[PDB]
Image (cartoon, grey):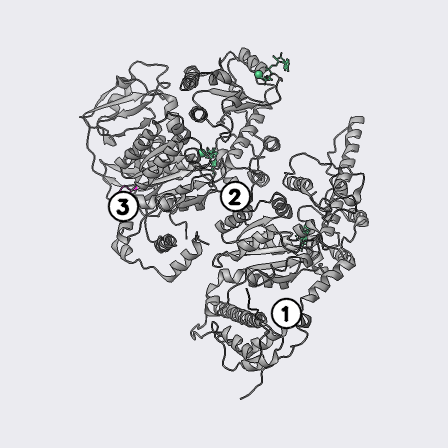
Amino acid sequence: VGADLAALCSEAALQAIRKKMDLIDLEDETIDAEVMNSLAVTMDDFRWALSQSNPSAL
Amino acid sequence: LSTAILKQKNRPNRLIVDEAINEDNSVVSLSQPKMDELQLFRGDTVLLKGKKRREAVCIVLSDDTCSDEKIRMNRVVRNNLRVRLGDVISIQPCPDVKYGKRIHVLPIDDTVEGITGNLFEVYLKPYFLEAYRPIRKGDIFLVRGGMRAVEFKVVETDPSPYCIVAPDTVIHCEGEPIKREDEEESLNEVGYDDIGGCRKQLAQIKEMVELPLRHPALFKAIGVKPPRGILLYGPPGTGKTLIARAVANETGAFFFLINGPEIMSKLAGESESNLRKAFEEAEKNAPAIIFIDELDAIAPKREKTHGEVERRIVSQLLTLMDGLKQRAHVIVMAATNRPNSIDPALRRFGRFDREVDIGIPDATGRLEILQIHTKNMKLADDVDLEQVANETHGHVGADLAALCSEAALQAIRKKMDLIDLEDETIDAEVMNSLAVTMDDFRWALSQSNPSALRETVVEVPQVTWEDIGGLEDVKRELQELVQYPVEHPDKFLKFGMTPSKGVLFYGPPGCGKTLLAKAIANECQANFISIKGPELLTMWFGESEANVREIFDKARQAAPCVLFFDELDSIAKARGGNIGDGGGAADRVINQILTEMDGMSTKKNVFIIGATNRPDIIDPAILRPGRLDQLIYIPLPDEKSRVAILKANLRKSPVAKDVDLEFLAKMTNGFSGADLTEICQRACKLAIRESIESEIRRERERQTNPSAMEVEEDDPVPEIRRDHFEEAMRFARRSVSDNDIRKYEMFAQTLQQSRGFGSFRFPSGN
Amino acid sequence: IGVKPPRGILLYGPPGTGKTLIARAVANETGAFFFLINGPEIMSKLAGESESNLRKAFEEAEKNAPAIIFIDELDAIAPKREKTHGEVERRIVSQLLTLMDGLKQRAHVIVMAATN
Amino acid sequence: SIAKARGGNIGDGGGAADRVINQILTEMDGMSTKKNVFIIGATNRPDIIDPAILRPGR
Amino acid sequence: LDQLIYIPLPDEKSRVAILKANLRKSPVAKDVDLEFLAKMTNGFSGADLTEICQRACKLAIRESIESEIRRERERQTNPSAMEVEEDDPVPEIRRDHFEEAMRFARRSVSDNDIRK
Ligand SMILES: Nc1ncnc2c1ncn2[C@@H]1O[C@H](COP(=O)(O)OP(=O)(O)OP(O)(O)=S)[C@@H](O)[C@H]1O
Ligand SMILES: Nc1ncnc2c1ncn2[C@@H]1O[C@H](COP(=O)(O)OP(=O)(O)OP(O)(O)=S)[C@@H](O)[C@H]1O
Ligand SMILES: Nc1ncnc2c1ncn2[C@@H]1O[C@H](COP(=O)(O)OP(=O)(O)OP(O)(O)=S)[C@@H](O)[C@H]1O
Ligand SMILES: [Mg+2]
Ligand SMILES: [Mg+2]
């Protein structure tokens, strides 16, 4: 259902964050704008998040 | 890479601790490139940041002999940063010291005994002045100016975080001393050091909580809403409240706690005041976390409750959950142990959509929990904690804490013939002579009662391919069915086939079907869920069918995993055998399995395996495509496989090196794996009989003859010899007859291809 | 040694085996400040009055740290919540849970109870 | 006793499994062997016993 | 339910169209003569033809992965050039896979059933 698709998009973008987390610092106060605008969600992110999600309408 | 939030981000300003060679109470010693890269100035103080948000400020020295990653500190700084040796400390330059006018230091009530006087005026009043000593709210400092540790606790300071003692810093000592037990309660707060065996779940909770709180700008700029409700579920005693207190001490965000029976214990119309007070107080201070412990006490299923005030409480909770906004930056998380007992209106989107499963810990988690709990026990060198963690099978962490308690109580009781109950005090030799041995754990483990044995385990098996003898063809074939859709999805995308979901093994009893399933689960590093015959029969007699749906949901939760249905023929054999009753070949439980199997998404990596000792009476509706498809026959083992089986079943026992196992494997033809295991077990039993019967003669002779008793020989029977195998080989038997093997061969030939089509060739036409 | 002693001890058995006898025996034995709670004596009072008695009992025992609290006939004051139909009884059960969890290692208080 | 009560040797249309012996097998496979509980069963007529009890581990 | 409709086993033209329809997902080679296959099979149903096509695709995937393992082992064993960057060894499944997979086909429907 549409809420599951919203959660799918959320988990794809979270995986896209986590692929950069080796560069991303949690402990510093701010984030560089190159790290900010370098985010681009790929097909691998959706293929991850679709394998992870659980549809509640089967 | 789902664990990258646990990494501590190694940076050049990160410093491991070191021992202070300078005994000043607030001194550190750093190198000149360290005091030039961060430009640390002597005369001001650094900003040290330690565990559990506890920080400290200290004067700095230009001692270049310290290494580039270390910093020297005494026990006072090890209290004020709350760190032991080997701990990392963040350092920051702080020239921002603002001074105070009136401070008010306070003693500790049990340290002030002996000589009271006013030892402040004697030692510690001219001790802080003109040394530029930085003070801080929460400074418990060792007193080396006095003759002993008559310590003070710096409590009241006109700057609340910290300051350097100025000439304007006027100190007053009129107040009461600080209690000891409250500070001992303060020294034992909980961080991530106390939690073991839950790295994955802690990573997920850190990703869901710590990241939206520290950086809302990341989610505002990417335009993605963080979640609002996180639900923790699991068996009782797995440490949910522990994780709550851990994140509560971790974040520094404004934490609030709600206890369920504390809400339900009050009068009507009073508990809703507490709920509204809690949410208004947390919305007053935006970086907040609300924790609700034991949620199922305050919101059950509304069909079960009979009061109306309880339904009013549930509706109040729903309204206050939906009234929460993205503006408030408030994360509401709750913990229960019964995920099904909750009113399903709370499960919906925007209320509680994040479910984290705190499961039963495996052996490595058991070892980590034992190492956490046994850090303050005087332990003997005999104690092997890994052996204990291997033997403790059904224990959650609270059971392991009770196990350590009972072991130490047995260690007390072994000295109780010396220990007096009636005297007022205990001697310090009796106190420090306590050392918990392996016998204490072997006692307490025999005494304890694990409250988790009625649970399905979800663990990676340790049975490798080396335990199984031979069978290289089905090894390659199971690799082809299981390992490549996991590893190489893109090849299945380049062509146009979908991988199969099912495998049916069939053959004689005791040939290694369960070992093959566990071995392929070990090879692909997936989880394993086993379901035996008696569980299916239990569902068939009791006519309970939601359990199958709960099983498939549990397997969906732990993906990737294999799912092993042992003995599918059990219900058919129970209802009529082959000849049957008046019914057909379908029933209730296998029907529910087919319904759940046709409805699972194939993009999940759940793979289903079913074993059968008698394949003719299986319902033929399972063998259709889209279901269990590949039929695999597993015969009796040949010579090389019997060699490997006899080798694998003897790695626990010490055998003698003149035993010729190849001769045994050449002599046996119709034996299965269970028969070889029976032979090995009878040999070990005869060896134990020989050992005990030999030691009885030793006891009788050494008590009958006290003449010398000097030689102290070794065992008469170590390393079991060929004589025991020659005796035990008499009682072996073939458990599988020839007509049974004939029947399996006939069913194997019924699955032959069409008798023809060999040497099929296209016409080679240019 | 750094080992926490237990907090709750439950005595169970058939009726007439002398549970109250063992309670009075340890009560005369220890010399610690003993207190007694009778189950139907708690349930016999009015609504909103029994919780006063429970809080009074726990505050009085936490006033004097070497204490033992004994609760006789526990099943009268906390049955299965699926069986009870009053709400005041569930309030009593939740009050007992809160006062049990509010107990600390500081208090040196051992709470033991007997049912059949 | 249950097998003799349900059909003797010739039986009814059913097989050789039932409810109570099933629950015994379920509880027996789940006990820890480090406990010293030892199980003994007597039989005056051993042919009609369920053969699932005679497997190893039982 | 009134109209009884009998649906027999497919003839040659229908087997041609079934083999064409079950292969639009996979890339096949153009020297495969599907009409010869449909002429050779008589008692096959649609499930049998789908089984043949699936076994052919499975053999093709085995050949591709077993060829790429040699590429990995040789390029890690020999770091000499690693320059050519060739295409797939097995794209577009050939007649050899059908000749191998046609051995394991069978008629799933006997003659007495069709007689019935
Ligand atoms: N993973 C763990 N690591 C260390 N200690 C643990 C762990 N799990 C449990 N414990 C110990 O067992 C205790 C159980 O804590 P609780 O949070 O009360 O248990 P629980 O999981 O919350 O179950 P309930 O339903 O609340 S009683 C903890 O206080 C620890 O002493
Ligand atoms: N190939 C094998 N390699 C090693 N041990 C084996 C093998 N086959 C059987 N065994 C042993 O014999 C017993 C049979 O275990 P299982 O794998 O359960 O046998 P099975 O073929 O699955 O059928 P069951 O379970 O006995 S009814 C175990 O004690 C195994 O250790
Ligand atoms: N072990 C015993 N030794 C001596 N007298 C005993 C013993 N057990 C029971 N009695 C006697 O039987 C009485 C029963 O005492 P109770 O404690 O009231 O019984 P109970 O075990 O508490 O069962 P209920 O459920 O409270 S009626 C005691 O007062 C004694 O007179
Ligand atoms: Mg808890
Ligand atoms: Mg009594």
Residue located beneath label 3 in the image = A29
Amino acid carrying label 2: it is: Thr
Amino acid carrying label 3: it is: Glu
Residue B45, given in percent of the width and then of the height, sits at 25, 36
Residue located beneath label 1 in the image = E108
Q: Report whether mark 1 lies on the same chain as mark 3.
A: no
Residue B77, given in percent of the width and then of the height, sits at 33, 32
Alpha-carbon distance for marks 2 and 3?
36 Å
Alpha-carbon distance for marks 1 and 3?
69 Å
Amino acid carrying label 1: it is: Ser
Residue E64 lies left or right of residue B759; in this view the side is: left
Residue B619 against residue C113 in the figure, above or below: below
Residue B351, by quadrant, is top left
> Mark 2 or 1, which is nearer the eye?
1
How busy is the neighbourhood of tag 2: few (under 14 within 10 Å), some, or many (20 plus)? some
Helix, strand or loop at label 1? It is loop
Query: Going by the picture, which residue comes out furthest to the front?
Result: E2
Q: Residue at x 44, y 72 (%)?
A: E82
Alpha-carbon distance for marks 2 and 1?
51 Å
Q: B561 or B465: which is nearer to us? A: B561
Q: Magenta: predominant secondary structure element?
A: loop
> Mark 1 or 3, which is nearer the eye?
1
Q: Which mark is residue B501?
A: none
Residue E80, by quadrant, is bottom left
Q: Is residue C45 visible?
A: yes
Q: What stretch is highlighted in magenta?
A: B325-329
Q: Report whether mark 2 lies on the same chain as mark 3.
A: no
